[PDB]
Amino acid sequence: VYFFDNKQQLIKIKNSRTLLQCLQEKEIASDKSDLMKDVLTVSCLHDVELEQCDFMAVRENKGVYSLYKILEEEIDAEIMNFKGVNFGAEELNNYVVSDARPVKKTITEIVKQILTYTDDEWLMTGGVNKIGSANFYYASVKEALKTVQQLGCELLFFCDIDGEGISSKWVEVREKIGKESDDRYEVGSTAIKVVKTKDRTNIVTSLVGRGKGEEVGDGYGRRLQFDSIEWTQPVPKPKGQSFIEIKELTEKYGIPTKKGKMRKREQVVIFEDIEDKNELLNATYQTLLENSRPLVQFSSEVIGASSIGDMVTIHDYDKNYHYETRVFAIKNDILNNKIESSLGDNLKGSSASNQLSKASSGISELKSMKMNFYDSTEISKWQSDIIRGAKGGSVLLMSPWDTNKGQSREPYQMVIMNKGSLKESNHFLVMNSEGIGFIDGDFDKDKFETAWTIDGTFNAKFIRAGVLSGILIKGNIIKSSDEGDFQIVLDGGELTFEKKYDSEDINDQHGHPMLTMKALYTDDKLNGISMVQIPNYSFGINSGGLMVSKPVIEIPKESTIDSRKLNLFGEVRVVGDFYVNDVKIDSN
Amino acid sequence: VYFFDNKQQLIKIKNSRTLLQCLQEKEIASDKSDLMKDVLTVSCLHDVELEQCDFMAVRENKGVYSLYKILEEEIDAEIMNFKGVNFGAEELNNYVVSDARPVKKTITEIVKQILTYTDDEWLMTGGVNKIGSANFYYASVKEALKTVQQLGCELLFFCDIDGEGISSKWVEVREKIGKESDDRYEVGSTAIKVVKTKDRTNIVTSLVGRGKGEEVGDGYGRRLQFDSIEWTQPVPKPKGQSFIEIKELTEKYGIPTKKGKMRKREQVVIFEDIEDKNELLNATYQTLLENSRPLVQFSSEVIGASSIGDMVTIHDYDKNYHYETRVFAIKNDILNNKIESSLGDNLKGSSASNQLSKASSGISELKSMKMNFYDSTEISKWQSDIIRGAKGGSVLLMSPWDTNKGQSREPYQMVIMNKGSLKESNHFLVMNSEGIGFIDGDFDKDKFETAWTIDGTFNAKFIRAGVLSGILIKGNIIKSSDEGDFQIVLDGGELTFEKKYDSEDINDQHGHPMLTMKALYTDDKLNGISMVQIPNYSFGINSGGLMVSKPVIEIPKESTIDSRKLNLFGEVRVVGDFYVNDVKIDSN
Amino acid sequence: VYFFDNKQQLIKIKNSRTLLQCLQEKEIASDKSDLMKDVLTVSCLHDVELEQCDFMAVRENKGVYSLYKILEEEIDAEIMNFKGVNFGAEELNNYVVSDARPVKKTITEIVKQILTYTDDEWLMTGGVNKIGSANFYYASVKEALKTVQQLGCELLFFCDIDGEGISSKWVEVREKIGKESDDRYEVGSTAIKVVKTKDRTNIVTSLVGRGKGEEVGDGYGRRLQFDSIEWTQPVPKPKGQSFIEIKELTEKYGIPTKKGKMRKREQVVIFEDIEDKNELLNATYQTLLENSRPLVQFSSEVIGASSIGDMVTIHDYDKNYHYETRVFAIKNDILNNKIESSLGDNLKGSSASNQLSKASSGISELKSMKMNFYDSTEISKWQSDIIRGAKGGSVLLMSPWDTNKGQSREPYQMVIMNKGSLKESNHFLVMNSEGIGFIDGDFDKDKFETAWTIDGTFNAKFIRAGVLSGILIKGNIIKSSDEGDFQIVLDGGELTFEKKYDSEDINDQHGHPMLTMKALYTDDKLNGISMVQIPNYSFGINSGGLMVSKPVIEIPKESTIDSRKLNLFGEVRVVGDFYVNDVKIDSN
């Protein structure tokens, strides 16, 4: 046993004539999410230059050495104990993966990508050709390797150690650990104390698959199922069924009935992250196939030496059974030449210590995979903001939070924009606490205009296209315009021909009258209708054409009540009474 | 001990002269959610034809047999070992219950309903008259029976076994297991080694109840309490208080004070699914009543034989105590005539193995009853959709998700319908990225018109009912119409009478002039008001009635500036000077 | 040993010549969230009057006594056993804190405030000057003290016990338990069996801190980090880095590389309730300083007597080491004068029982601090109601739930109010399933108007301010009014002067005609423009001023087709040929 100091430099060599204990253990875990266990324990007499050492290594052959790092020492009386684990499981826990996210790549490329964060110290050897994906964010490298291991790969670690330090390190990726060995164990000559165990707790013949939810929120707990999938060639499955059954397994492990017939065994299997149907069926089929036969375990003391993970054959001639199994646990005592092994399926996972470890890991996982009050509030806020329109399209309910991040989220106005989003649109229709208004080019709030007011006072200037029909007009003042200074007015049941004037008041629209057709309250009754004239103005009933207009009656500018100067022009044929002197007399 | 093969056919009988161990254990669990434990263990010498057996049974009396299913087997030193459990706890785990949901029914009917999923194999015997409800979805029958058992029933299982297989199976429902036996145990003659234990850990005299939330979201953690419920006859409880206290229990187990008085003990009890007040009070009262006395347990070796669940009486004359207890655990050894029993309240739930089992079950329950990111997102989406209007009432915000299910959830228009929902309404008011518009009968076809445009151009054709008053009209063109071809036009500050015409342009409304009362720019000043005429048209100031109007002045069709033929008609009284051959005249 | 009854009255004294066992244990837990352990165990021969006692006490010196409360009692064979804990840890579990919520106060004031719920039985002694805050709701006092202890204080409990009961109780608050003692332990003379353990499992040199989320909802898992904080004087930390590193620790405990250089060790530390950067950096620095050196533990059997928590010194001359450690566990045996102690850092937390207890506590905490279906639904409802406007501002989508609390949540109308909320505003713009309408002062009523209708029918009476221009008017009836009974009408392609009238129909607006400027269908062609008169009415073309208008032609009330009476007034100047019994005449 060679001991190294903190810089991995050789210090001392301990022989086999001084050590009091030397034990090495290896074990392949039942689950695929755990690494391979490797522990060494050595204890010798107390020394003063062995309390600074941090590494210890043993010998496999002339070219391969295994390195163990001390985790704990215990001086008792004068005997120093020690305890070590593999170097890789302790070194690869101090590299941080910021964020890595492959999508549908092979395992070899994923390992290449992960081992980039170790700064070229670690390499990799071997390959697998299965495609998978994962999301690695802030986490250690060992956890990432654990996650990769679940896809069907098994990992090891090695060194190239000399007396002056470590030179090269690499990681081997394989499918199954161990080649096939030419070993032969016989009970009574090579295997000494054989204990055979058989278990039948978990046996199924039919399973019902379930998926990742259908309509969550109703509370009815629906899940995706393979109800309407046809699948014939591997195992005949009908179209109206919802479970996979193997016939012969039912005949061999079924529940007998009254009539001598057999019935199947059905248990429910849940997959939390399956969204398709065919892959759910494949997963359920694999789960059914894995759990169809009882488990067998052999545990014994052996003479011949085998590595971990080989295939060996064990025989027993007195009771006449013959099996082929796979070594999965080895406890090698170097000092006393005693070797203990185990073959077959692993049933060591039901001991108390493993259960304690699994419970602690489960608590630690649940603490990080579930959502507390803050996360629920944040998710609700995000999903409400998505539908309110605060991130996308043309309809939006504004709140001060959308502008300052600091005030309340309470809405005070509703905005309909032109295109896209707030910065991508040019026109706005705003509904706020002042009335339905409009906003110009930019939403820096040029100035808010008003079309409707909340008390209900429409603004008339917004009528700019169309034809008006089918209504009544009353009380209003009408007017027209020309290039000169003449306009027609209808104010208070009056027709006014006057001169133009520009103003901003209802009363000030009226100008200087010249001719006003009207009516007069004639003698306490409204039976007088006539026009009027005004002096210094010309009036007429001019006749002719569009270019020429000659006076039928000419009204002078000086026409007055006193100066009744009733000019007339034009050849007029006057049928009716005529006047020269006194008394009416007829004509032509 | 009789051994059966995989089809429940008798194979071999083993005597008592060749067995090495036979042990049978029974135990009633402390909690009501666990079944009754039944375990048998037997070991004999190795045999070839015993490695295929799957059932082993023992004898109770001449008509009752108990059947055990082998779960494990272990050849160690040609000494085979077997371990078995009850058949019922293993067979009823392979029957899937899908979607069974009773509401407010009796336990007997619930068990009858559950046992219809076993295909007539299992029956039921007995009954309990208590009302309860449960929700069973995809799950096995055993878990359903476990859930039912929590409502105040206790279950057993039985068979009717013969040499050629099982004939009938049934499940018995009871209130308490065991009748009242006539047995008497005396210490020193019938009971050998007696160990008595007394516990005082959980002792209370007052409790404060809490309910299923009040206003969750504030984060203040309010809960429903019985603050304002009066309850007098069982135990006097005032109105202003929020806890139940029994006086004598306080006097007997109260904290002494400085003045020699006693104080109560208060602890908080939480019920997660209580929504009313009186039932919360009843539950708190029952919890208080249950936990008011210290616990006692007896464990001893017994000569006499009793079944499980009976009521036996134990006496001790030297120390002078006499108690009446209930048997709850029996460990019967058939081969050596040794019986071990326990009496009183169960305190076996604090051992390490039970704690490990409870921790595993608790973790597995938490993994299923708490929600991750996906469930929170789905619930938020559902609750946002409810309030957006996408499922119900008359105000709704459209998004592409509501029509095509594949695009984003971002809104782009707001729709107000007529009645009900999208398919139950005929008329629509729509405000989208092109202005306030309207939609006809069917919404599936856009057919979108516009009333307001986002730049603010109202369409005038939408004014169809009302009276218009209190505004000004300027610049606009006015027109009327009749059945014939006459209309009145006010264009450019002139009154124009023409012939009617139909057109679609502002300029084309004007027609063929006949008489245009207008004004003339008379000598660089606007003081000329006059009419005009046009040849080949008739003009007049006709006078008379509504039927008839005769010309005061008749304007001929040929009236012209050149041909000044101004025909006049009617009896006229022309007072004033006149024009006859250069003289002034008078009234004859 | 003195035994008390249920009222804490002395009953019996047991000497040292009758007891069979007496053992006292004390231990300081590794975590700061657990109290100080104190356990006593005594056993003696069975006595009749010792089965009612509930307290047993021992002697420290002539003035200090320790009180223990019996929890379990076990009569076995003829020897009674007992098991007691400290009085305080059992008494202070029966006082209920309703709600206390201090903010940024000192520990002394927090303890003072908490100890007001014991009704002046418990006092306080000592003090610590550090500022902290906590939120206490319904919970017992012991959990509150546990939570306070996490801020850097350590608690003890005491009594003033006499033969007639307890007189005064108090709690001492300290920062560290134990003074500095003048003790000297030498191996081989005063310490007998020394076992030393050194642990190196968790050693780090650099850490990466994380905070309380950044944008939860995207699913990317961002967290607050100290990326852009400069912090130099304690440890030089640059501006572009995301971790804190100590140099010399890396030089002493670093991973050696190929070229002889050393590398750092990084692990991720998560704080779930940190929102600022400088405090996150401080917490990470404190963790790094706490986890930088390996741990050492001494366990031995000593001769001299020391209290719990002192600082002693242990020496060993043969192996030449000298350490200064702190006592943390004492197991004093009173009957046999044997004392067993432990020194240094506590490594007793990895035993099986402690792990079981921690797992149970973790499950119980997770069950209470996570959210199930009901909580998620309630939070989503609250956060949707906040943004819908149902609590605050001036835009609101009202649903029947907002008024009756019992019906569904689907919205049926949208309301825009004036100010604040429903009760603080006067004018409303309501958009519902009937049309865009308005509501007067109070909203509790249903005085709903209708401007728009869903079929697109505007109401013309809502135009009340503005100027109308740029449109066309067609078909509509135009009218005016005056104080008298005259109005100008333009209906059916004609101009009508008539008498004013009031009505509510389109047809009834027309009145009694007087003068109707119109057109006549003159001989199958529309070339006739004419006016008419009506008998018993006066007509004229009056001329003059605004005050005076004299008839150019006077039309009498009796003017008729038969009674042609065309009165003319005013001195005329008439050029033309005239009618003097035929031919043609001259023109003055």
Image (cartoon, coloured by chain):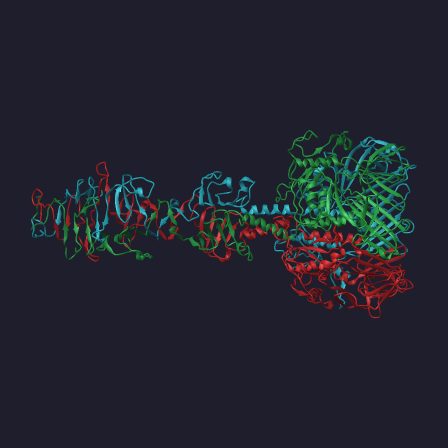
Chain colours: A red, B green, C cyan
Point out residue B217 in the picture as x, y percentages from the top left corner. 61, 45
Of A187 and C159, the residue lying toward us:
A187
- Residue C559 image-quadrant placement: top left
- Residue C167 image-quadrant placement: top right
Is residue C30 found left or right of A106 in the rendered image?
right
Above or below residue B285? Residue C282 is below
Point out residue C443 in the picture as x, y percentages from the top left corner. 48, 39
Of A310 and B350, the residue lying toward us:
A310
Of A129 and B17, the residue lying toward us:
B17
Point out residue B395 in the picture as x, y percentages from the top left corner. 50, 48
Of B93 and B349, the residue lying toward us:
B93
The tally of labels here is 0
Q: Residue furthest bottom?
A: A62
Point out residue A581 in the picture as x, y percentages from the top left corner. 7, 44
Is residue B200 found left or right of B45 in the rendered image?
left
Q: Is residue C128 visible?
A: no
Q: Is residue B264 visible?
A: yes
Is residue C398 found left or right of B46 in the rendered image?
left
For the N terminus of chain A, which image quadrant? bottom right
